[PDB]
Structure formats: structure tokens, C-alpha cells
Image (spheres, grey):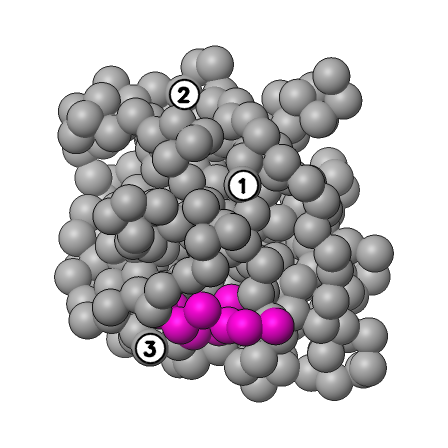
Amino acid sequence: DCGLRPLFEKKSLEDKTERELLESYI
Amino acid sequence: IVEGSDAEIGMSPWQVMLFRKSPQELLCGASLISDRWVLTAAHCLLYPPWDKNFTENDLLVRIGKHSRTRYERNIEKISMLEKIYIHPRYNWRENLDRDIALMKLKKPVAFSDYIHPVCLPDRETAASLLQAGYKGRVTGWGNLKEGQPSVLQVVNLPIVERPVCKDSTRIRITDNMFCAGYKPDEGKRGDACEGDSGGPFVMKSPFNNRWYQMGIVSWGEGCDRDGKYGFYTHVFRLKKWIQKVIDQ
Amino acid sequence: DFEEIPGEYL
């Protein structure tokens, strides 16, 4: 169930800077 | 972490604190990979030039923390190690090549909102995300300055192109390493630092939305120095030693 | 600076 965070991924909420990561994978 | 921000609650539920029983103190970070297995830098356990040779009996593993120094009653789980394994070809004499170690917990930890494992990359994840430019995330309770956080800090940093890494130092860089940071020109800063060692360098897969540990905070020259970078153990290149110890 | 931890844990 690895790498799916209970308070973020599991509830479909984003953390405050994850966007900056994904935006870099072009 | 130098130039990081406070982590939010449950942002890194795989973050582990390596803690010294006596004198009670933060040794390094680590990450939870399953209910019984913890991953960290070998130099956290064994480093002969500094008379560092820690045994199982010598430490605690603290999972689900936010606060660096509080005992987070009802949140955090503190465990005891059943066994420590260091990479047989770890190089503490020349460059910290293969800086990796597994810790077997004396008993499984229960998952929760604040406690949850990270994924280990498989060949295609690594192939796709380990790219110059691609950002990863480092977390830890280390020094804020080449200065002690009150709470778990975080910073997003770019992976740098192999050659730029070689050229920044006099140290012999191997294939089990990768460096990450901002060029002095990019005019952005941030870096692991004293205390962060052994923590995770993770990326989020754009394909399945999972977080993967790509590196382990291994070494650096100063903290957030211009034109120097952080060096990380390449978890995928050491993936078979990992499977191996777990499976036997 | 570290607050005290339960003895069961040592």
C-alpha cells in the first residue's frame, strides 16, 4: 500500500509543494 | 535542511529518527520500507575514523514524529532493533561508496495516519524519474545552518547532471551515487545538513501517484555551499542487496 | 533538549 499517504493520497489532498515536483517531470 | 520549510503533518509518514539511548540524541534519519524494516546510511552506524561503531543495543528507532525533541504521546512509536546489516562493500575508507544499511525491528510497527511506508523503485520507475532536472524531496531534523529545527523540515531539489557533480569535488564519485542541488546561478538554495544524514530522497511517480525512495542522504561538503552538491546513495543500483537480505 | 521517553522503551 506503499507510498500512498493516509492524509494526502488516500483522501485525494495534495501537499503544499508536491506540484513543484510534478511540474519538473516536464 | 538549509533553506527548507516546516513539513505539514503526515507529509512524510515513512520518516524515521535514529536515536541514541545514552546520551539520548538524534543520530540520523532513516525511512520505513515495511512494518519491520528501516533503511539508512551505513555511515550512521559505522564510521571508524570517528570511532563510530554503533550496535543494535545502542539505539532506538522513532516513527511518526513531527517534533524533533518532544515525545509525541499517542502519535509516535519507538522501537528496538533486532538486527543491523551494513552493505558488505560499503567504502568508509575512500568515498562512502555503498553507504546503505537495513535495520530489522524487534517487532512490527502498526501503520496509521502518521506511520506509513515508502515504495522502493523498480527498474522502470528509476529509469523514468532519475533525470537531471527532475526534482526530489529530502526531509530531516538536521542542522538549519552549516540551527536546530523545532519541527521536521523539507526542501525540493533538482537532480544534477553527472559531470557537474564530478567537477564540484576532489572526491571519487561512483555509479552508486547521484548528487542534487541548485546551480549557484539558479539562485535557489537548500540542502541536507548535520543530522539529516541517512534520510530519504523521494520522488512522486507521475504514473501511479506513489512516492518512491530514490536516494539516501549520504554526504556533502559543508551545507548549502555554492557550487557544491549533496551526494546520495542510489537505492535502485543497490536494490538486489536489499531484496536479498529481506528474503533470507 | 530532548524530553524524557518512557522507560519501557529502554
Q: Main secondary structure of the magenta part?
A: loop
Is residue B73 on the magenta stretch? yes
Mark 3 or mark 1: which comes first in sequence? 1
Mark 3 or mark 2: which comes first in sequence? 2
The residue that disc 1 covers is B80
Chain assignment, label 2: B
Quadrant hosting residue B235: top right
Quadrant of the image for the N terminus of chain A? bottom right
Residue at point 70% right, 20% down?
B244
- Do tags 3 and 1 sit on the same chain? yes
Q: Is residue B43 left or right of residue A18?
A: left
Chain assignment, label 3: B
Is residue B191 at least partly visible in the picture?
Answer: no
Coordinates of residue C7 in the picture (x, y in percent): 45, 54
Chain assignment, label 1: B
Residue in the foreground of this view, choosing between B50 and B192: B50
Coordinates of residue B55 in the picture (x, y in percent): 39, 27
Q: Which residues are magenta?
A: B65-74
**As shown in the figure, which amino acid type bears the numbered disc 2?**
Tyr
Coordinates of residue B179 in the picture (x, y in percent): 39, 47
Q: Which mark is residue B67?
A: none
Q: Which mark is residue B90?
A: 2
The residue that disc 3 covers is B150
Coordinates of residue B120 in the picture (x, y in percent): 69, 44
**As shown in the figure, which amino acid type bears the numbered disc 3?**
Ser
Residue at point 20% right, 39% down?
B169
Q: Nearer the viewer, mark 3 or mark 2?
A: 3
Residue at point 37% right, 42% down?
B218
